[PDB]
Length: 517
Image (tube, rainbow, N blue to C red; front, side):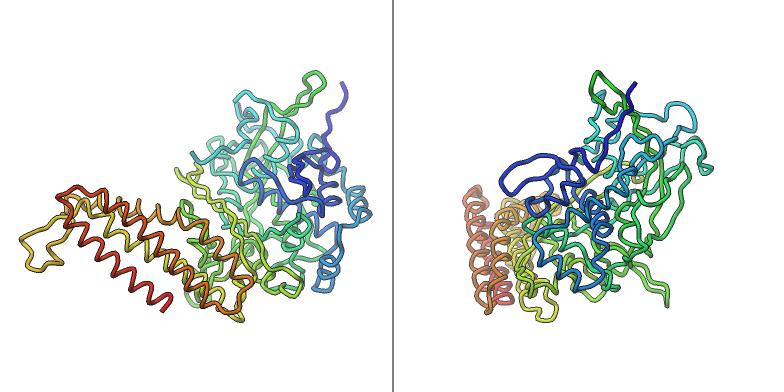
């Protein structure tokens, strides 16, 4: 029987969108050679994009042998494409490590991996992630994409014990969630994939932003792994970006002329030392959680699921005293003199339930952000952007007085007209849920206007004008919603509409004076 092979450097498996509109899969060689002709990744599931971007960045540092510094970065930015000769010299040296079905060095796999007991091998559908809320074999390209994703985004369900792992007890060895599932990921995206890769290729000289260097090598340059695992500090970004967080083996099968993957074994792998990750990783911001003398703990800053990403703009910009922005944003902040006005910030975060076994929520978004808003030297642009979010939040809160009007009482046991107009205790939880629903409705209406406002800050000198424009837009949206809700009141709730509208209008006026005097 002929040998099964699938060389990831020369076979198509990375879905991209081309500048001429084509949508197709490319090999790792073509994703570099054609990076200046590609818009970007065109993936099918949100966790795939950070995982595949970080894989491709680890490969870029190794192919380019840099950038070590600003001068090297500058010569890459000023060039129009990546060197085919650099790319082909690298893949000629390492393509014996890019075969998905190699019998000795299967890519991101353990060649001899076996279950510790009976039933550990599962159908290949277990490698596929599904939305936060079975016999289909995978193609080699699908399996490769999910393999890259699973090492980074796996859950504590990947507990199947591996033979030869002496940590196995009760037939299992339970891992932590994957490292990308743990961090709040943020990365800039340019107009082409080549720009995106360069915006993320922080030079090694930025020791405050990343750890990288000549000795920092990715997983496929290291000795292949076995069933044993460790907790280890990453050597740098190439190591971290290709972290073998799991121990996986694909079981391919020939079906006529097609190679497919019907089965897989997924076990616990290496854990990232979270203290060392903070020094290495440019795609995560941090908040200081506790300090006891010299002992300090940090937690990742996280895009909150269930809200539009600009509502958490202060968690992106990390402007509080206990917060530190993603090192990639500090790098991009210094690139205005290169002709870059805006970047699209890709944000992802995850939330798990049931002792880290189930993916309960996934935050995934893109925000078009001016480099002017990233400016910490002159903070006026960031200040108007954050203040505009605060004004939206105050308008949503003011609308609560109208949302609750249908539940308001006129209670004669109180002796002040303001205290008589109240929600009775038996309707408090319902009125609170109605206030939240009307707040969510105004945020949905302010989404496309906020994004337009934020993009417009890129080319404005006098920031008092967009501050006044945003104030009038939010008021107009808030009064339209208030008028619709008041018109729906039953006749016996007319008094509640009068009180509610007055409270809404006074609160809105107070917030308006604080935002745009």
